[PDB]
Image (cartoon, rainbow, N blue to C red):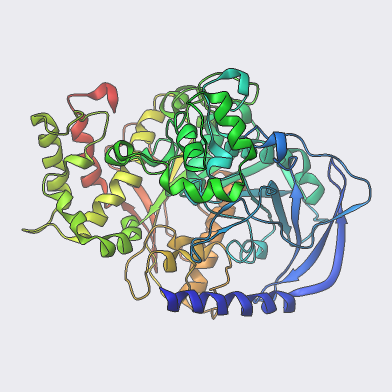
Length: 565
């Protein structure tokens, strides 16, 4: 809406001046393996303080011949690199302005801590942002460390290449563009963190990686790939994982289509296509991505044209040599403590889409288009496919006529709950007993929000949508100082506290977190038929996952196809 665009611009300006008033005149120098960096001490609105290093390069700028290639190690420097200000985000369409922004020069991470010379080495928490592999950033207007730095941790926020610039993939081995450049960026950042966190007070023997949405899929990929074996010690998957249907795609044939949209006049061979794309303006490629998917791919419900892919040939930096379902079977990360969770109304995220085209509710008449693609016939007309759709329909259509709320409830399961069930069950076959803990974020407030609520046209909407929990982990430009006694402030304390406790010990329970006294938070066992989770609302309560019945109804579609579950 034009009104929300104006209110956003106003908030951008007020936030810029708030950030000036939160900057002190105290700067500090830290060591890295590539040279010295200068950071600055900042305040929060709660009068905590932290040292801030932004714009630390973990790779060469991926420009010129390095476009579409795996990241290369950065060049060291003499002197002191200024890390007192942020760098640009990866080239992307701005989620509110509707225009391309960012730069190819985006391979940076930021480090935050309340004390550069602590008395004891600290848990290191590494956040990988979401945004469907096409948007996102580590700027503090979205991901402020202000809540975590209340406690004695080191927090690190990474960037990685997005869209076609991060995820182009070509079959021809001679061209060295196998795919997943953006995931390889994440690998290089994690290697930097392992080798450098001690210079900021961090414990390289106690690193936790976490992320939400595509950042959860990313964290999971970082737990699956051999490239990162042993680099970190706990993982937290917030509303996503690497076997979600939206988390990967085979995009090798789409480079030609993108080139044609950008003015390419030649034939479909990888060498000529790549040479054209190497000369194209990066803003043009990113703007045209919305047009890349063909009529057939849209019909088949492919979501994004470029993203994580199974790489077509092996390279030294290869991240995904097989489908993630197969990678789970040998994954090093199955042996580290893991926490997984979702919000209590994930699919509310699709509110504005159902407002744009209300006829989507007609998809619930047969639900044939929601049957998992590995179970469905090509036409989605086979009797078995319709009987599977009828099972989906009975799980989510609660009244005589399907409603938008029924549709959004279905979305919660197809995109989040069912893939998490499938992952837990697949993983129980390939782990030596390392614990996995479930949470359910169920705290609803409009007094502390984040920019995702604007994206989903969620003002005035009740329910705990996808990404609503981020307001309780990170300061952002729409946030405000909350009273100590407020339900929102308590939720910040609880969410950061649980994450820090888990990062420290691999067990998310602590009697020092308020309202967690009487909680017995046991991890999921292989023989459990019903998952339990810590439900986070105004109270903290262990419950059987309310979504279980529906999860089991989705699982029942595989009763005659157990090999595919």
